[PDB]
């Protein structure tokens, strides 16, 4: 199913996944989400502890709980508040809820609860808990990373409402944001307990590294969730969504499905190799917090792959069919023969 991914990076699991799973489930249960057992099962299928624990396998358990908890509520946000509710006024309802969430991260006692709100109390709890470990610059990074995610989701809902297919150039730099890469990883330096110097985090080389890691992970997410996209489309009697690297290359190259999967993986291999090569040049002068950051990006790439191929989120999607979708993967041990920049301008500067 998925042609050989080049990813010569070790992957490891956090030893306290079970503890994290238990507290996560308990923590999200103490608000007012009114979670059905079906909903609690899908959350288990999301394996938030397995996902973040692979990003940070050596982190202390009580601090990792912060990042894990966030994945918990943002899987629920993703599945209940993204592309759902009435089609009439759908964009307005998203943007309204998105800006509330950002504000609560900036001001936990803003009290922006509307009628029937159940996505702000846990976000507030996360903000309050994040203000006990994090520097001001850190908090600011979480808010603005949430803005980047949500602006990209507004972009995404436009395409879903039109069933359009984004051109490759546009998708190639937007996908890191619809995937919430930066918002997902911004918790890591808070868990680590040391501020990454803004001067480093803003340098062009680190920005390339950052966007390489998040784009790669999101393209992989597109790969290991392709089956689900095919299942959903088969169930709903529609064509697969254009919001996905495979379908975009299909439409762009007027090719068949297998050719598109090979092209998608070829691209992923080139991004991954570029990320590794650029990491080599950056490491020597890297402060310890930046090194740690690159360490988490390095665990993210193979960790995301292993999570996505094994998590029930993408195998038993509705929560009632064990093995409806099965997805295979290989590891290509050879680096890509072509190390030059792809013909995708919106991202070419990563090879600068």
Image (cartoon, grey):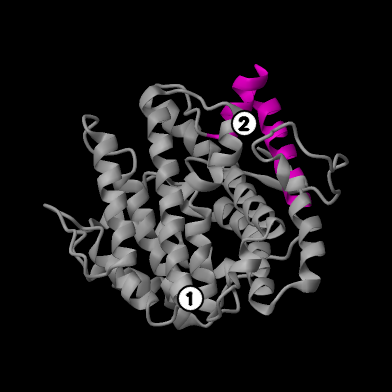
Residue 3 visible in the displayed image: no
**Marked residue nearer the N-terminal end (1 or 2):** 1
Who's the residue at 42% across and 33% down the image? Answer: 232
Q: Whole-percent x and y of residue 286?
A: 73, 73
Q: Which residue is mark 2?
A: 169
Q: Is residue 250 magenta?
A: yes
Q: Whole-percent x and y of residue 322?
A: 45, 48
Q: Residue furthest front?
A: 199
Front residue of this view, candidates 263 and 4:
263
Is 254 left or right of 61, judged from the image as shown? right
For numbered disc 2, what is the local secondary structure?
helix
Name the image quarter holding residue 31: bottom left
Give the extent of the magenta segment. Answer: 244-273
Mark 2 Cα-neighbour bin, 10 Å: few <14, some 14–19, many ≥20 = few
Q: Are marks 1 and 2 in contact (CB under 8 Å)?
A: no
Front residue of this view, candidates 279 and 140:
140
For numbered disc 1, what is the local secondary structure?
helix
Q: Which residue is mark 1?
A: 64
Q: Is residue 242 above or below residue 181?
A: above
Is 66 left or right of 262, judged from the image as shown? left
Mark 1 Cα-neighbour bin, 10 Å: few <14, some 14–19, many ≥20 = many
Q: Nearer the viewer, mark 1 or mark 2?
A: 2
Q: Is residue 335 magenta?
A: no
Who's the residue at 25% across and 68% down the image? Answer: 29
Residue 160 visible in the displayed image: yes
Q: Residue furthest top?
A: 254
Who's the residue at 29% across and 63% down the image? Answer: 104
The quadrant of the picture occupied by the N terminus is top right
Q: Whole-percent x and y of residue 294?
A: 67, 66
Q: Is residue 41 above or below residue 91?
A: below
Front residue of this view, candidates 134 and 156:
134
Name the image quarter holding residue 26: bottom left
């Amino acid at each position: 199913e998925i042609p050989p991914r080049y990813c010569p990076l070790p992957t490891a699991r956090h030893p306290d996944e079970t503890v994290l799973a238990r507290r996560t489930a308990d923590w999200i249960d103490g608000f007012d989400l009114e979670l059905t057992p079906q909903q609690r099962a899908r959350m288990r299928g999301n394996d938030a502890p397995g996902f973040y624990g692979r990003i940070m396998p050596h982190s202390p358990t009580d601090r990792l709980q912060l990042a894990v908890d966030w994945c918990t509520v943002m899987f629920h946000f993703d599945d209940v508040h993204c592309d759902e509710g009435p089609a009439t006024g759908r964009a307005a309802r998203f943007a309204d809820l998105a800006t509330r969430i950002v504000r609560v991260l900036e001001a936990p006692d803003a009290r922006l609860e509307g009628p029937g709100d159940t996505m702000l109390a846990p976000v507030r709890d996360l903000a309050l808990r994040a203000r006990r470990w994090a520097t001001p610059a850190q908090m600011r990074r979480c808010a603005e990373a949430h803005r980047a995610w949500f602006l990209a989701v507004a972009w995404e809902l436009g395409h879903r409402a039109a069933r359009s297919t984004p051109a490759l150039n546009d998708y190639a730099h937007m996908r890191q944001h619809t995937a919430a890469g930066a918002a997902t990883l911004a918790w890591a330096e808070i868990v680590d307990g040391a501020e990454i110097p803004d001067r480093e985090l803003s340098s062009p080389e680190v920005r390339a590294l950052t966007e390489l890691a998040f784009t790669t992970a999101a393209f992989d997410d597109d790969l290991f969730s392709y089956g689900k996209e095919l299942w959903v489309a088969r169930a709903e009697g529609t064509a697969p969504s254009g919001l996905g690297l495979v379908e975009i290359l299909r439409r762009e190259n007027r090719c068949g499905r297998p050719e598109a999967l090979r092209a998608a993986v070829c691209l992923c291999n080139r991004l991954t190799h570029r990320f590794i090569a650029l990491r080599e040049r950056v490491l020597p002068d890297a402060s310890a917090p930046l090194r740690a950051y690159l360490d988490h990006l390095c665990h993210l790439l193979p960790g995301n792959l292993e999570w996505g191929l094994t998590a029930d989120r993408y195998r038993n999607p509705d929560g009632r069919t064990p093995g409806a979708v099965t997805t295979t993967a290989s590891r290509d041990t050879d680096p890509p023969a072509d190390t030059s920049p792809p013909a995708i301008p919106s991202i070419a500067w990563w090879w600068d």
